[PDB]
Image (cartoon, rainbow over all chains, first blue to last red; front, top):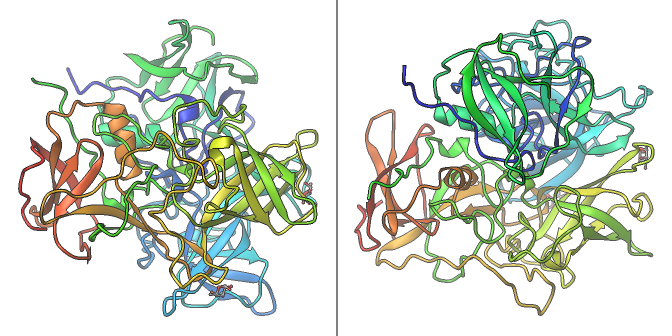
Length: 309
Length: 309
Ligand SMILES: C[C@@H]1O[C@@H](O)[C@@H](O)[C@H](O)[C@@H]1O
Ligand SMILES: C[C@@H]1O[C@@H](O)[C@@H](O)[C@H](O)[C@@H]1O
């Protein structure tokens, strides 16, 4: 009784960041999810500040890789032997699904591989793409592969970084049928079982749906599905981690307030395991004031009935 | 008296992010600064949460640009007519030096320009470089130029984004003599005066130097100077903005604690206007435990004498 008061930050949606790719939030979206399994590994955190899945604290690290590269002779492809984010040796023994910040969806992520030669400080950067559905995508084992636009420029045994930019669609896939944001990679490679996963989430209360914090990933080629939905803004992960306020019930009731009118636009349930639901049936792009923000009002139970969104 | 207690977050250096480029912090550095003018515009915030210069809240937006592009015929160069970060019209009337997150140093920043065609969702991405020392670099006026590897692929009148990756050195400049991290761009173009700047900072107390929060920018070509020093971690900007705790004096005394020993490694002054000094003379790479963190201990005056670092 009387535990440290819980709260959410006073930040607008546009002031916040996707927790699944290093891009700002744009909008709120709700829709049915019974046709897929919603089990992202980034953007996972309890309200009392326990990080889950592959979630870490800074959004700039999400979908980045570091290590050194080995040329696949006769190609423009390179295997990256992963390092830790601080350039130390990779330690695969942590009880996590994959290094923190590893991509948590199947898709073709395009970005840039950069490298510095230690002896002289010479540098180089080239377009690179990682296919996280590849049989050889095995970040938990410390290896991933990049397709690049060079077969000779990258040196072995030198620090190399991948900075993500966006996603592509190619290879005869159907328009907007990739990336597949709700398909988890096999983190140890094809036909291995993922471990230490944050659980799947779903609305369980009749008439409820998940509320998604949505961005549009940049597209780099083809006709990709650029929608990217996270369960928590990165800033909420950061805030809960720092506050570590105890949950007094299973559900924190939040009101989304419009400062231009002083009135509540909608209310929602922030589940203590770290996801949000609203009372709505159907796909809906929420129309919000850009200065709107969420406000924690009370601890309720999972069987509280929300006002329709 | 009795004002809301000030604090800094319990985050390690490696858990934090540079406030001047979207990359993690790596280390702490101190050195003399009397030979340059230290006046960065990103990573500027008072301890009571007032954002300064071009500082905004999410690190992923730093050094990004959005808008639409106009091809310079007979070249592979494009002028970007800037939009707001949320894709609304750019409003140059705000009393800021340039759009929030604009680069605050002179250098050649390489990244990727991406574009989506609205009608069909077709996408494209190409290597692009902005030279923030260019006479035509005029983000405050809503204009910047990109050199790319195409003269035909980018459409006019479509949403286009620049995602930064790193820096280059070329054009016969001396090795490691660019970027110039302490040279501010002319935000309205060559021979215009910058406005609404966060002030220059310097140590004033004898025997003190600035403490810098340092990263290494990726290099994309040539022999760039990749050192990037910020005055405050991005997470401290975020935290002070959210806490808005009043400063009880000009200086917050912080101790850097080593949890592996329980002892203080060094102490430093966090000035209320948002920068840090230490008692040291000379260039020094601080050797810190990776789990070390800063802790606010007391309000002191600017005339307090620190223990030597
Ligand atoms: C769908 C197509 O994808 C890539 O080939 C782009 O280079 C084209 O401009 C177009 O967007
Ligand atoms: C200094 C040089 O810079 C660019 O030309 C790179 O492509 C080279 O590999 C080398 O790093």
